[PDB]
Image (cartoon, coloured by chain):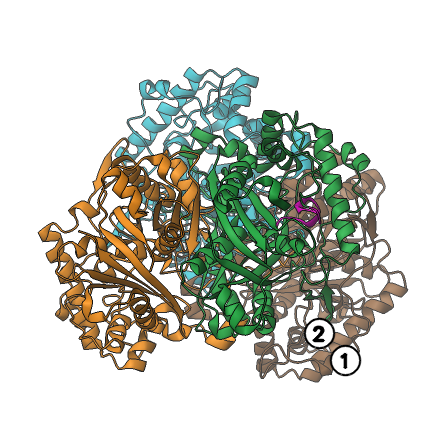
Chain colours: A orange, B green, C cyan, D brown
Amino acid sequence: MLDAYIYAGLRTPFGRHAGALSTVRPDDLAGLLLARLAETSGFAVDDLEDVILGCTNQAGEDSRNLARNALLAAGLPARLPGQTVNRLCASGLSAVIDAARAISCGEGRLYLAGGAESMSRAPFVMGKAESAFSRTLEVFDSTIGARFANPRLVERYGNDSMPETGDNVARAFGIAREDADRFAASSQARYQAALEEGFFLGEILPVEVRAGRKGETRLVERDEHPRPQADLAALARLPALFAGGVVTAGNASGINDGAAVVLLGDRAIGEREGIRPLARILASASVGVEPRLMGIGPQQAILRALQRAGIDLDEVGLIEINEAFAPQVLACLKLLGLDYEDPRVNPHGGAIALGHPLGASGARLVLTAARGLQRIERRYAVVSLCVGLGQGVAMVIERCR
Amino acid sequence: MLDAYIYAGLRTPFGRHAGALSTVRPDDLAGLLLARLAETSGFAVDDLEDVILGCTNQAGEDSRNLARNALLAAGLPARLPGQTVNRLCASGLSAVIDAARAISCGEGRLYLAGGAESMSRAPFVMGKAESAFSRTLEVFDSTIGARFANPRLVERYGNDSMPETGDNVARAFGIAREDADRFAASSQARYQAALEEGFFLGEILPVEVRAGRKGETRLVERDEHPRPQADLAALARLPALFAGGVVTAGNASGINDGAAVVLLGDRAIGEREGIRPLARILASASVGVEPRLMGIGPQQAILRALQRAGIDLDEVGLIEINEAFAPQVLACLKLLGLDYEDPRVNPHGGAIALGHPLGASGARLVLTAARGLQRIERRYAVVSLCVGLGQGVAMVIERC
Amino acid sequence: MLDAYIYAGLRTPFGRHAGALSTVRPDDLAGLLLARLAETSGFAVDDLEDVILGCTNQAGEDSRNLARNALLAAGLPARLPGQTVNRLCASGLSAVIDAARAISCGEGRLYLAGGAESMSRAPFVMGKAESAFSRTLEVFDSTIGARFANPRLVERYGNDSMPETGDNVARAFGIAREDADRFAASSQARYQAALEEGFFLGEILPVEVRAGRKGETRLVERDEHPRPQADLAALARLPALFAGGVVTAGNASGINDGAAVVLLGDRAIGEREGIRPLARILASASVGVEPRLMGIGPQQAILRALQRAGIDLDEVGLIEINEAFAPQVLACLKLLGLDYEDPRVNPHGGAIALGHPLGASGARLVLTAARGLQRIERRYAVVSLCVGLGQGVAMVIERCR
Amino acid sequence: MLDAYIYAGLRTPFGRHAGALSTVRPDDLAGLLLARLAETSGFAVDDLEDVILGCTNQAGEDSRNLARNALLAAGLPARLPGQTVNRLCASGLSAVIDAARAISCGEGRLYLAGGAESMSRAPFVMGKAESAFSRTLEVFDSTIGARFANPRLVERYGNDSMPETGDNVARAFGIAREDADRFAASSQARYQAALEEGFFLGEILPVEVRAGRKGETRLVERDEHPRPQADLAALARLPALFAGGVVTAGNASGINDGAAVVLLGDRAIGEREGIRPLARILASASVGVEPRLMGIGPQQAILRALQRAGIDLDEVGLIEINEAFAPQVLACLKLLGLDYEDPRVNPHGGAIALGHPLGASGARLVLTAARGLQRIERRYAVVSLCVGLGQGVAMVIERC
C-alpha cells in the first residue's frame, strides 16, 4: 500500500488555445501555484523535498526542466530541487505517483507534484541537417500530434491521430455517436451545475494577465473551455472529424493552457504540524495497450490499481476518467460494466467542458477527486487517463476525515 | 532503505557531436539496449512493469515520451508502459532512482531504467507568434544552453553558462588550473588503462551505423570522445574559454550521443529465476544549490545519501562523480575532505574522456559503478552528478 | 533622349505594417492594378509586350518572378511575359526605366511597369547547414534590414542600419533635428491638403480585404500611414532612434504594403489609338555612393539625369525625392542649392506621410509626378530615390498636353 | 536594331548540388568574375555604368540586390551601381538584354551583365503568422520548386513541376524517349569533345575553395556536373521520374552552383581603347506561353528575335537552346523545322552535361555563343531559354 497524503492543491483556470492564458509562460503558470501553496499550506518551505511536474512538450519556455525553472521563477528557495516527468496525457498523474512512491519509501516528508502545459506557446521544431546543404526540412508544430515519427514504430502500429483512435474504440466496442453526444452534453451540464454550486471556489487560483492596451491587467477567474450552450441537440448537428467517424469537435476535448499542483507528505509531518490531509494515496497502476485503441488504457489500469488498493469498484464513490474523447470514456465504462451515465463519473464535469492541457489534466483529476471525496458517503476515488501511443494510468485515493 | 536490485545493464559507445552515432535516432539508440536486455537478461519480458528513461531535450526524435517510442520501435510488447524523466544532467540517475522507489513500494517486480541523448540530432526550436505578422522570432539550438530563458530567473540568479559555473566554483573553493588539468589527464589515462584491461567489454553494446556508401555498414564498438594524447603538458597549453577562468575545452566534458539502461527488480524475482543481482540500491538524495555554483551539487547529495544508506564515506570503495568540468569535481572532493587524487574516484575514467550525452550519463555511472564494485574489496559505491540550474543527485549501492 | 510615354497608372493605398493590406498577397495586390489597367487603358491587351515589377524581397508570395505570377493570377493572357527587378528602394523606378529603355530601342510598343512590396507578409529566412548536424542557425526577418551580410563587405563599409545612415548624412552635411522635424510636419500637412483637394482620386485603386468575421469584406480607399496630428510640436518631443542622433520614428518613413503600376508605350501606338499620354520619359541616371551616406544618392543621380535630359533644375516644376529620412531629403536639397521648404518638393506629401513599401515607392513617384505635372506651368518633373548600400536613381519626365 | 557589343566574359565552373562550389557565397562567386573582368578587360573601371545580375532566388546571401553586394564585396568602386533581375531560367540572358538596351539608348558606354546562383546555399523560407499563436507554418526550400503558390494561379494553370512540363511537351509534340536520350548522349559527348579540344580554357575562371583541413585550399577548374559515362545504352536503362513520362534524371539538367558575366559596351569605347569586340547584340524577344508547356517558349522567342535581327534561321551558324529537359529542346527543334541532330545546336554541350544554376545559365549561353562564333563561318548565333510559368527569351548576336 502506498502511504502518501494529499494535504492541499490548487490549479489555474484552463484557457482555450490563444485564449485567456496564452500570454503566460508555462513556467510562470506553474510558478504561481508553487508560490501560493508554499505561502499558504502551513508547512515549512524547508521541509519541501522536491517539485515534480508533468509536461508533455519541454521544447519551449517549459524546456530544460520546467519544475526547477518554475520553482526558481516563483521565488522558492534555490535549496529545493525539481524534476519534470513525461508520460504524455498521464504526465500530471505520473508526477503525483512518483512523489507518492518517494514519500512511501521514506525519501522526503513533503513534495509539490502536478503538471503544466502551454499548448498556445508550444514552439515550432526543425530537424538538424543530416548532410551539408541538405534540402529535407522536417518542421513540426509541438502544440499537438506526431512529430519526427519513427518509421519502425509506424510500420508495426500505424499513424492514427488521437481523434482517429476514438473512432477505432467506438468501432471496436460498439459506442454510438448518440451515446457519445449524450455523454458530451452531460459533461457541459455537470460543469455548469458544479460552477453554480461554488464547487470550484477553493480549487482555482485566478491569474492576472496583460489585458493589452498598456498597464492594463485582467483577472482570469474562470475556466474558458466550457460551452454550456452545447446541449444534445447542438452536438447531434456537428460533422464527424473523419468520414464514417463518431468523434466531433463537440464530443472531444480541446487544446488548452493550464497548471495544477498538489502538496503530498507522509502522515507524520501533518501530525507534527497539526495539519489534516484531504486524502491518502493507496495505489497506482500503469499499463500499455495497442496504440490504435489507446483510449481503453484506463480499464486495465483501474482494475490493477483497485486490486493493489484491496478494494472493489462498488466501494468507489467517485471516478475521474479523463474525457479525451466521449467514445473512449464510454468504452472504458462499458468494459468496467458501468452505465454510461453512472453518477460517480466526472460528477463536476470533465475535459470536454474544462479542456485538456495535456501535462496538467492528470494533476487536476487528483485535486478535484480529493476535494470531491469530501462531499460523499463512500471513502474511495479512482483517477485515470488514457495516454497517446497506448497507455493507461490509474490511482486509488481514500478520504481521511 | 531502498530495496531494489541491479541485475544487468548495457550502454552504447558514447559518440562525438556529428560523430560515430550522429545517424542513430535517440529512440533507436535506447531501443537497441531495451531489446538486447529484454532478450538476454534471463527474465520473462512479461514481468517488466515499466521503462523509465532520462532525456534532457524531448523536442525532437526523443519527443512525445522517448521511453514508450523507444520500447515500441525496438519490438518490446505494446502491453509495456514507459515514461521519460528530465532532471537535466542527473536525468539517467533520476530514472533509476524512480524505478528503485517504485520497486521498493511493491509496484512491479522488474523495471528498465536509464537515459539517452542525441545532442547531434537535437532540433532547432522556434517561438510561436505573439501577434499577427510578428517580426520577433526566437530561434534556439536544443543541443545545449539556455533557450527561451525566463526574465525573472535571469534577474535573481544571472545567465552564467555551465563552463562559467565551473570558473565560479574554482574561484569560490580555490581550485588551481594545474590541479584541474592533472584531474583531466588522470581521467584520460584511467580510461585508456581500463580500455586495455578489457573493463568495457561487457558494458558496451556495439552499434551498427550506415557508412553512407549505398548499403555499407560500420560497427561502432569504442567510445569516440577519449583523447589518449591529452597529457598534463598538452592540457596546460590550451586557453581558458573565458578570461580569469580555469575551464578549457580539455578539462571539460564534451557534447555527445549515447544511451545507457539498467535492469532493476526486487530480490524475489532473481531468487525465483536463479539470477544473482550485481548490487542493491540502498538510498538516494536530490538537493538544490545556487545555480551560479551548480557544480558543488554533489557534496550535500552525497552526504544525505550516505546518511540515508547509514554508511561513512570511509566504507565507500568506488566514487562516480560526473566530470562536467574538472574544477567542479575537485571542489566536490575538497568539500568532502578527499585528496584530489583519491583512487576510488572515476577509477576507469570519466566524462572528460568518455563525454556527456546529458540524459545517458547518470545511467552510465550506475552501470559502471555496479560493474566496478565486482572487482574491489569495499562493498559500497556512491554515484553523483551536478545539475544545471543548481542541483545534486546521489545514489548509494552495495555489492550483492 | 529616351522616347517612352506614360499613358496611365494606378496604385493601391499604402497600408501600415500588419495593417489594412496585411491579408493581401503581394502578387494579388500587383495583379489588381495590372487587371484594372489592362481593362480600362483603351489599348489592346495583345499589344502589351511585357510586365516589369520592382520587388526588394522575392523570398515569399513575391518569389519565383512576382511580375509573371501577378499577371497570371490577375487573369492577363499567358502570352504576356514578365520580369521582376531589384535595386532595393529604387526598384519601382528602375522597372519603369527598364521598360522606357526597351520602348526607346523599338523592342515592344507598350509595357506595364511598377513595383509591389508586402512588408507584412515578408517571410523568415533560414540558412542551409554548411555541415551535417551543424549547430549554427542564421535566421532573419526578410521584412527589412541586413540578412546574411558579407563579412568582406562589412569590413570595407561597416554595418550601419538605414536610420543610422540618416544620422550620418545629418552629421556630414549639417542638418539640424529642428529642420528635419519641420520637413516631416510639412510632409504630413501637404498630404492632408492634397487629400482634401481630391488630388489622390484618380491615382488610388481601392482594395477589397477580408474584414474578419466570416463573409465580411471592407474597402481600403485611403492611405493608412499618414499622421495629420504630427505637427512640429509633437515631432520635437520624440526620442532619437540612436544616441546623439537626429532620426526619429516621426521624421523617418515606415514599413508598409502597397503596389504601383504605370502603362508606358511609344508615341506611335497612342497616335494610332487616339489616346494621349500624360508625359514623356526623357532620361534616367543611376549612381553609387558610400553605403554609410546612401541618402545623398539622389543629388548626383538628379544632376546626371537633368544633364542627359538637356534641362536645368530651374526649368523643373515638380521634384519627387523619396522621403526615407527627413535628414537625407534635406541633405539632397542642400547639395542641390535648394531651400528646405522649396514648394516643388513632394508637393502632395511624401513617404513620411504615405509610408515606404520599398518596391512600390519609386513607381508611386513616377505616377504622382506625371499626374502632378498636369496642374503646373513648368513642363518638367524629376523623380529620385536614395538606395540601401549607397545608390541614387533619378528620372526626368516632360508633360505632353 | 540593338547596338551593344560583347567585349569579354568569364564564368565559374558550374558545381553539383552540395558540390565543388557549395562553400562559395553567390555574391562572392559573382564578385570573383566582376573583379577579374574589371582588372583584365583593358577598359577603365571608371567607365563602367552599372552591374546587372540575374538571380532567381534572392532570399539568402543573394538577397538585398546581389549585383551591388557582389561588386562591393569584390572591391569594385562604391561609385558603381547595380541591380538584380529575375525572369527565372532566362534571368542571366535578361540581364544582358537590359544592359544591351541601356547601351543602345546612350545610357552608359560599358556594363557588366550576367547571372549567379547558389542552389546549394539557397535558404529555407517560412511564412509570417497570420494570427497570434498560429499553428499554421508554411516552410519551403528556396533551392527550387513552387513555394507559397497562389491558389488563383493553381486553379487556372495547374501545379505541374518543371519535369512534368517536359513530359507534357513530349506528349503534345510527339517526342520519343529514344530521341530524348540520344540528345542527352550527344550533349555529354559534345561537352567531352570540346573539353579535350581546349574550348573552355579562356571561358572558365578557376575558383579556389576550402578543402576543410584547417587551411587547405583546392582549385576548381572543371565543370563538375558532366557524366562522360552516360552513353545512349546507360540512359535507356534509367526510369522516367513520372509514369507515362519520357523525362529521367539523365535527359534533364540538374541543380547547380555557378556564375557567368559578360562585359558589354558601345562601339566607340572599344575604338577609343583599341579593343575589338567578340560580337554585336542585334535583337531580343520575350514571349509568354501556357505554363503547362513552358518548354516550347524558345520557338516564338527565336522567331521574333530573328525577325527583329532581320535574318533567316538559315544564316545562323550556332544555336544555344538551354537543355532544361532533352524533350523540350527536341520539341523546339521540331517546331522550328530543324533535325534533332542539327550540329549548330549546343555544339560544345548543354545543361544536361554542364548543369543549370538557374540565374547563371542564360549568361553562360551568351558567353559561349560569342566564343563559339569565333570558330565558325556563318556569323549569326541565337541564344534562347524556356522559363518556368511559361516564357521564352531569345537574343541574336553577330560576330564582329
Distance from disc 2 to disc 1, alpha carbons, whole Å, reads 9 Å
Judged from the image, the secondary structure of the residue bearing numbered disc 2 is: loop
Label drawn at residue D234:
1
Which of the 4 image quadrants contains residue B182?
top right
Q: Amino acid at mark 1?
A: Ala
Residue located 77% across and 32% down the image: B236
> Dot 1 lies on which element?
helix
Q: Nearer the viewer, residue A30 or D399?
A: A30
Above or below — where is C342 with respect to A100? above
Within 10 Å of the Cα at label 2, are there few (<14), some (14-19), or many (20+) other Cα atoms? many
Label 1 neighbour load within 10 Å: few <14, some 14-19, many 20+: few
Chain label for disc 1: D
Q: Quadrant of the N terminus of chain C?
A: top right
Position of residue B173 measured from the top left corner of the image (x, y, whole percent): 60, 27
Q: Name above or below for residue B398 compared with residue A336.
A: above
Identify the residue shown where x is 79% and y is 60%: D223
- D1 or A241, which lies in front? A241
Q: Quadrant of the C terminus of chain C?
A: top left
x 60%, y 81%: residue: D245
The residue where tag 2 is placed is D250
Q: Choose the circle earlier in sequence order: 2 or 1.
A: 1
**Can you give x and y, in whole percent of width and height, for residue D29 in the image?**
72, 48
Q: Chain of mark 2?
A: D
Side of D128 relative to B322 (left or right): left
